[PDB]
Image (cartoon, coloured by chain):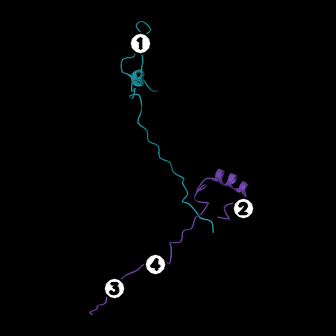
Chain colours: A purple, B cyan
Amino acid sequence: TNFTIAGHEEFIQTSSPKVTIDCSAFVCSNYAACHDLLSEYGTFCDNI
Amino acid sequence: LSGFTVKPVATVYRRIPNLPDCDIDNWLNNVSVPSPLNWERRIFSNCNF
């Protein structure tokens, strides 16, 4: 017999923060002896 | 591309001494010069030189 109008909110996730990782500053930041052993693995950090 | 880092051409060293400072090695430079008659002797224990 009688009516009104109600409201409702909804949130849908669309984006996400983009994260970039570097091997040269994670495992072998500033050590030369570390880079010598890391080069033995070859194309292993280029895939990450 | 590859990164870079500030050149660390400096060093800082700090450490609390375990044993207390001896400061007795100056006994050889006192004002009373000994002689072969008495030739007083002082023993050093728990010291750092």
Is the residue marked by circle 4 packed among few (<14), some (14-19), or many (20+) residues within 10 Å? few
- Picture coordinates of residue A8 (x, y %)? 36, 83
- Residue at point 32%, 86% (across, down): A6
Measured along the vertical axis of the image, is residue A16 above or below residue B35?
A: below
CA gap, disc 2 to disc 1? 72 Å
Labelled disc at residue A10: none
- Residue at point 36%, 21% (across, down): B31
Residue wearing tag 4: A12
Q: Nearer the viewer, mark 4 or mark 2?
A: 4
> Outermost residue, bottom direction?
A1
Which amino acid, by three-letter code, is at mark 3? Gly
- Residue at point 31%, 90% (across, down): A5
Residue wearing tag 2: A43
CA gap, disc 1 to disc 3? 100 Å
Residue wearing tag 1: B41
User: Same chain, marks 2 and 3?
Assistant: yes
CA gap, disc 4 to disc 2? 38 Å
**B41 and A45: which is toward the camera:** A45
CA gap, disc 3 to disc 4? 17 Å
Q: Secondary structure at mark 1?
A: loop
Q: Earlier in the sequence, mark 4 or mark 2?
A: 4
Q: Nearer the viewer, mark 2 or mark 1?
A: 2
Labelled disc at residue A7: 3
Which quadrant is home to the C terminus of chain A?
bottom right
Q: Nearer the viewer, mark 3 or mark 4?
A: 3
> Outermost residue, left direction?
A2
Q: Chain of mark 2?
A: A
